[PDB]
Figure 1 (spheres, rainbow, N blue to C red):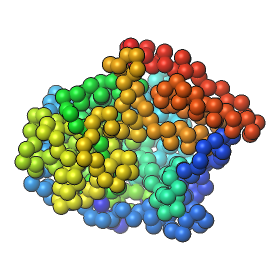
Figure 2 (figure 1 turned 90 degrees about the vertical axis):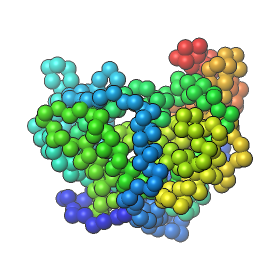
Figure 3 (figure 1 turned 120 degrees about the vertical axis):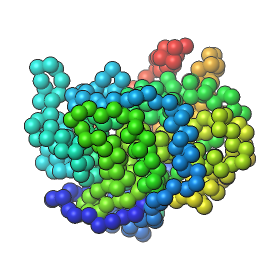
Figure 4 (figure 1 turned 180 degrees about the vertical axis):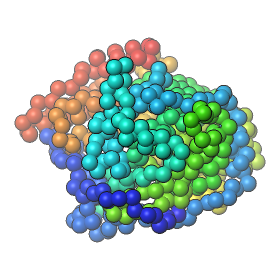
Length: 471
């Protein structure tokens, strides 16, 4: 991306420098390979400056002109999508939801400048209809955003567990939140698109809105015409996305989305411009990012499309690419793809280096791509695909054991049993006795700390999984 000067928008917010993650009653259970990310510039665990490292991948440059295969990739992706005319959501639908899209999370931040003196719930009144209505001040900001999407993302250091290597290097990610009036305006303009995609994960090359327990089965079987399936990940995807890709997507969506009379006719392109030419506030640092996208559900939908377009623009340069025999599945920077004939991720990586700012790598910190790869070797959202031993047509999402082995050793301050319960939903897919080994190890450590954990029985988790997957 490219970082530009920006006029301040008011009183600056505060960047939290202390982690909410504290050691849990199970902290000694497994060898500690993860710790809370560096948030303070004075953290003793690192010799680096976190504010410097966290922004080091930004400002590397933006691409304004399309590379020769980019426009063909745009046409190819939208040709396969075959979207019918889409419409906008009403303001009340964008707030409270539709049969195909849930309402907003009232517990999330209200964003700038609301998040200075007010939370999200305070800005709404429950009407006699039983739905949430915006207060007269929020309604007017949503309206003004539809005519001029001028708003600030609040930027913070993401408080989360990280590998001990990333802690020592102060490599902590950024979390950026849009304001509530920009979110509701965005759910109005693009809610028809969000409905179509979020309610059909696996279609349009996007996995956004998926439930891994349920969708791992159709995801798995969708890659069955292919002998080789590839996984790859982007480093600094949210900074390296060029403006030109978002701009081209906005022009396609402008022709698809039908606008109501109260909305200016270029609102689609103008809102997308507020995404790739965005305003940010990080503490008292006010700046504009040209290129990239702040790292939200709507942004994950557009990021999926960006990822699909970018990958297709790489495959279109391969001499043997069959424009009809391919499938892509994306969630953010996470990607599965397969082509016939198989295109090795080496080829995509080399094309990206010569024409874009994308730096692409294996999905398992493997530092190299395997010579071959199948649906059984691949990981997607940190999960393998493993058929059930008794009903092999149904596929378990088997997350890496490091996920729930490390997470259980930390808490954010709630009832610790809630941490144990939510990890049971991830861990039981490893098999009844691998699940038991995790439960037994966690219980022995908790006993020394004065806590008695209760684990959901394996029979409950396996039955309910088979029930939802339609067994």
